[PDB]
Amino acid sequence: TESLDLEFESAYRGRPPWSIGEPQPELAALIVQGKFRGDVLDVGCGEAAISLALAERGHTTVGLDLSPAAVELARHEAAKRGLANASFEVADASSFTGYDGRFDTIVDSTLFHSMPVESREGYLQSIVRAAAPGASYFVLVFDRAAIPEGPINAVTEDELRAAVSKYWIIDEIKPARLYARFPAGFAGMPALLDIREEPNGLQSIGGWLLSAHLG
Ligand SMILES: Nc1ncnc2c1ncn2[C@@H]1O[C@H](CSCC[C@H](N)C(=O)O)[C@@H](O)[C@H]1O
Ligand SMILES: O=c1[nH]cc(O)c2ccccc12
Ligand code: NA
Ligand code: NA
Ligand code: NA
């Protein structure tokens, strides 16, 4: 068995490197292409920068996270922005109900590798249950070539395709960057991970961007 529940709750209570204060750039590029339609589910939402950006762009949004501290943070930023159309709830992405056929777009911003491999089927069944016909699904996930076997369940391209294609029609899988703001000396000196330094004091690690739709 494995569980990261306590770690995520502690990180949110205190800032997490992944809470970059904006949607992940790879996902913001899909938003500007018009790929996010209707009601949006931000699954494993964390502080929910992408929900909040979509709720500013006319969408009704729902963010789900297993961490109560993440949900508090997302609600607190929605309050600062006066955003009545963004809502958040504590829920397990691998086993949630209450949204049958609701969402036209479901976005997984780095939740995928944050649950055990054995929870993926339940998670994929749960988001399909919450999806309206023809819904789009976008996943940003770490690459197993960058993140090893351990607490994080990063994926190879073939592994990701095999898991998701059982439930969705895949349109594209391509290499992507996952951005973060890491502390100085993160993962050692020399570093044990390949962390790319980016402009604006950000960093990135290799991943995959998957685009799919309900068949
Ligand atoms: N089973 C599960 N159900 C729901 N959320 C989960 C979960 N397992 C992990 N999470 C959440 O998945 C998130 C991964 S970190 C990414 C958070 C956010 N999407 C962003 O891009 O900033 C965490 O907030 C963690 O609490
Ligand atoms: O899941 C993660 N754990 C710890 C990190 O610092 C991190 C940084 C970026 C993205 C994801 C993660
Ligand atoms: Na939009
Ligand atoms: Na988890
Ligand atoms: Na690219």
Image: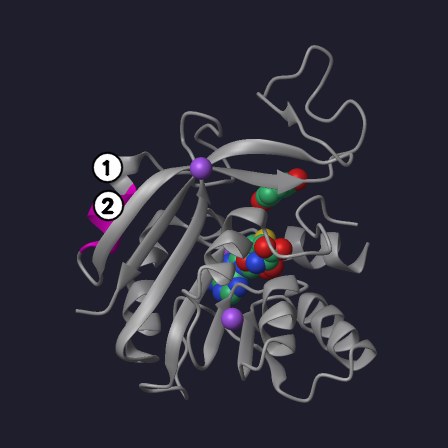
Vertical side of 192 occupied by 202: above or below: below
Residue 155 picture quarter: top left
Given residues 195 and 163, the one toward you in this image is 195
Question: In this orientation, does residue 110 appear?
Answer: no
> What secondary structure characterizes most of the magenta part?
helix
Q: For mark 1, what is the residue?
A: 158
Is 162 in the magenta? yes
Q: Percent from the top left, x then y, of residue 99?
A: 40, 86
Task: Name the residue: 55% across, 55% down.
Answer: 28
Given residues 215 and 70, the one toward you in this image is 215
The stretch of residues the image draws in magenta is 160-165
Given residues 58 and 146, the one toward you in this image is 58
Residue 76 picture quarter: bottom right
Vertical side of 64 occupied by 204: above or below: above
Which mark is drawn over residue 161?
Answer: 2
Determine the secondary structure under disc 2. Answer: helix
Horizontal arrangement in the rendering, residue 86 relative to residue 105 (left or right): right
Quarter of the rendering occupied by the C terminus: bottom left
For badge 1, the amino acid type reads Asp
- Give how far apart the Cα atoms at labels 2 and 1 are: 5 Å
Horizontal arrangement in the rendering, residue 188 relative to residue 123 (left or right): right
Question: In this orientation, does residue 201 appear?
Answer: yes
Q: Percent from the top left, x then y, of residue 151?
A: 52, 39
Given residues 79 and 59, the one toward you in this image is 59
